[PDB]
Image (cartoon, rainbow, N blue to C red):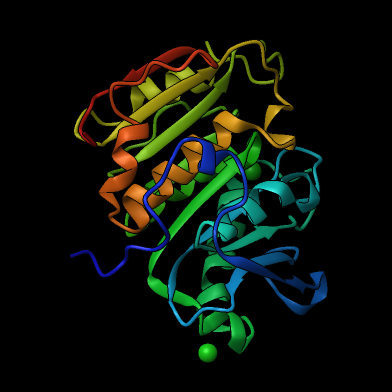
Length: 257
Ligand SMILES: [Cl-]
Ligand SMILES: [Cl-]
């Protein structure tokens, strides 16, 4: 049962480190693509399976290297992951959405044959930090064929996204760049009631929490991607009846349970 199932039965502990798949890396140079600023693809190797794909945007003034740890972590749990560089480091959230859109088309159509051989382009998802997270909400609303969206410490001036794509938002309690009361929590609140949605808030963490290995971001991002990109109900346990000391808030409409 479940053609998309990959990897062993999960434990929390296994989800805080790199997973069972070996990972290859391919550098997409800036000038080799129109529509975004290149980036790095992390993708499984040593395997004959196909996997869902994820496009992920860094944050304001940031490089793709800021999220390398998470691109590798995801790919090692069984995902083809393209972390973009933006055309300009100063690009805003809606610009980042359009570049996510270009990056997804690139992954499907024009990436190297070794990458395409590992990708099931029918199952794609998006994630992003800061302003990249605002771009994630924008594209989830523009393109409801996506399987999931994970905005990390997100920032946007627009507060309402009418999307049927399942969304998990990571807020940081002590974020002063995108305070959760103005950004993350309103985005959560304003998503449709019928859309499966989760908000998790990291205790004593600031806007830079996504820039380095973080156990909570690892568990919740892996689990949400697994549950919706792979229909993998083994990951429901990490997302249901949550009692996590690392979190200082938790909200959900509990549609995913
Ligand atoms: Cl913009
Ligand atoms: Cl092959």
